[PDB]
Image (tube, rainbow, N blue to C red; front, side):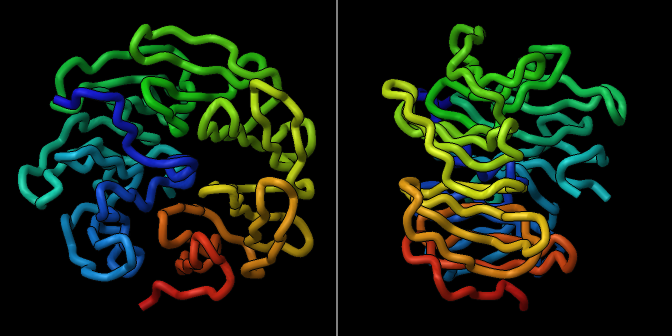
Length: 295
């Protein structure tokens, strides 16, 4: 068992289908050139090799294992999915929860996830990393994608505010007064969210010295963050994947079209064309030229 509050993935990856997971110098990922199957590579895109024939999403990792949701037969609705585990070396594949689920997120020794009660009714579950102690935590789902140490953060379903759940005490409380969607808290001084009151424009704030800054135009669909750069999809009449620094500077349009599933690693930021399902990437530190993952 884990001895600290390890987090299975980073920033907004799990909101963006958890297609890439960087951990201790490797990246585990869903390979769009091979039916979304689980692969591994070194952080710079080399040494690419198949880990499992399972199609994988919501990929998480700790020092010993990779945890993932597989589709047994889109990432954000009901399908015949199962929660699984494999050793990082490729051995020891096993199923932890065979029942449909999405949004698996590792916090310490527990995976918190969305469980389907029916095709439309959902709840929050957790399970220990060895498959013991499966338990329904709430009758309504709370977002578990954004984690830091023992906490996960979410828009409160009743009131829209940014709340924090402490997995150690198994309690929750208000974290920041806003009306938010897919919040990404990196630390108490770096809060990001789509602001429901401003048509999902992205806002950045430090909760200690709150001076909320709006960083984008209205009508944002997806975003992610690495370092001080925010990568986002702008919708509407002239859709584009864009980047901007967290002080409003350095805006750049990176690709024209409708993209999604923005996943960040220290080397690259990956994104998929919503219609063609083709995948692309760009440098995380100096985003500019776009590489294609196909073939």
